[PDB]
Length: 119
Image (cartoon, rainbow, N blue to C red; front, side):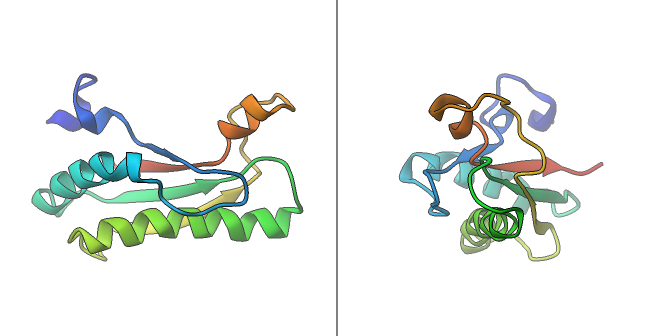
């Protein structure tokens, strides 16, 4: 199972966004296509698409932005033929920062949507 392989494209499971943006950049097409191909052939595989944001803005606002980012990925996967029974788009907002810095570099690491495969 390439999902356990660290040298497979399936190892990359994060989509990053620009400030205040929930648009899936073109550079993530290959990543989404690959995961789409894997999920479609493994219909028993479920994933949570977890949207995240940087600290700027209110919690309420970022909770919404985080959801928009997760759903942008989800729609991308849906468009590629992934079943609606395999995906759930959720938002963590700015609750769970992965980088604690207060700079552009740290913030960029928090504007993210994760493909989290369930057991």
